[PDB]
Amino acid sequence: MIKQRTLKNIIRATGVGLHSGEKVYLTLKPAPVDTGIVFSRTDLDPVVEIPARAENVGETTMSTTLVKGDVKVDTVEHLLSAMAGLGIDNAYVELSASEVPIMDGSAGPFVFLIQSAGLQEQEAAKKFIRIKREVSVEEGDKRAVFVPFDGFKVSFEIDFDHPVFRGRTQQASVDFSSTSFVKEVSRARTFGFMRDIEYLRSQNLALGGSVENAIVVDENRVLNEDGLRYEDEFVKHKILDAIGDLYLLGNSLIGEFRGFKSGHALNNQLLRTLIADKDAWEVVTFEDARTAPISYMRP
Ligand SMILES: C[C@@](O)(C(F)F)[C@H](NC(=O)c1ccc(C#CC#CC2CC2)cc1)C(=O)NO
Ligand SMILES: [Zn+2]
């Protein structure tokens, strides 16, 4: 039996918002069975809770944002990617400000803090969304597609005409029957281009960004003096983002995702189209883990 998982102990962390530049205190807490991931703005009275679900996604221009009325929770995809890769079904995410801390720009710090606290399996079947039919959305030259697949794999292809990508292709495929999310995906940092940052800051965006929490690229080079963690770190973060955006479905996926220059906006459009086309998916459990198409590491 593949059981639901929550946190064994609370996780506490402080950081800065990538776009707001605000200092934020973060607390992850255990949650009962079938709670899902629920964000909670504890700086407000009364506290405002936003379930990390596709129906609550607001603006998506920079990062994935959850909204409830006039209240927002910004930049959720990196923490949600850590949630998905670790198999965490239920948790409360308390924040003292509107944006999740960026940490080092990747999901690595979140993954380490969670695994240091430990996970707790719960006495209930883990629910999966199994893709039954192909579902694709396009807009312009961008495309995102779900494909039936007995497992979970993610492929992505970006097409930048930038010298930092000169040499090789900008494509990567990850199949978690062999790829380690922790070792090969979680540490890929977000990236920004120096030409955009001065404009972004003019619009009160990317205010917390620096070489401490992002790969900074000029017209030719990565400016971080210590370089990259992966040779293909850029596309690996696109895969990291997709895994986090996909977890807004509320359950782990049994299927294949393929992204072609897709972003947070098209990712959410794919989820909304999938959810609406109930012929294309179903909820499944596995009463015997030994016959499941996926497996999780020990809690
Ligand atoms: C990677 C992706 O482009 C992805 F969408 F492709 C997207 N990155 C961003 O938005 C983004 C990342 C970093 C900065 C920055 C800074 C700085 C600085 C100091 C030196 C002046 C700005 C924007 C993402 O990860 N969204 O979730
Ligand atoms: Zn990102």
Image (spheres, helix red, strand yellow):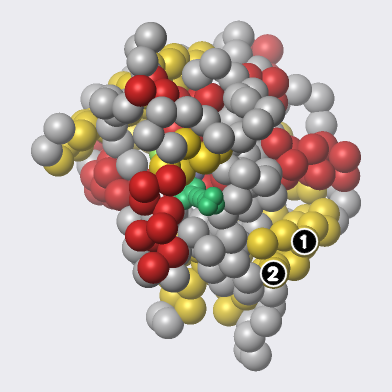
- Label 1 sits on residue: 14
Residue at figure coordinates x 62%, y 26% from the top left: 227
Side of 60 relative to 37 (left or right) = left
Residue 191 position, x and y percent, is: 49, 39
- Label 2 sits on residue: 23
Find numbered disc 1 in the image and state the secondary structure of the residue it sits on.
strand
- Which amino acid, by three-letter code, is at mark 2? Lys
**Are the two marked residues, 1 and 2, in contact with CB atoms closer than 8 angstroms?**
yes
Q: Nearer the viewer, residue 183 or 282?
A: 183
Residue at figure coordinates x 69%, y 50% from the top left: 103
- Mark 2 neighbour density, 10 Å: few (under 14) some (14–19) many (20 or more): some
Residue 217 position, x and y percent, is: 47, 36
Give the total number of marks visible in the rendering.
2
Q: Nearer the viewer, residue 167 or 277?
A: 167
Side of 216 relative to 85 (left or right) = left
- Identify the image quadrant of the C terminus: top right
Name the image quarter holding residue 39.
bottom right
Residue 76 position, x and y percent, is: 54, 54
User: Can you tell which mark lies on residue 286?
Assistant: none
Side of 188 relative to 4 (left or right) = left
- Which amino acid, by three-letter code, is at mark 1? Thr
Q: Nearer the viewer, residue 84 or 286?
A: 84
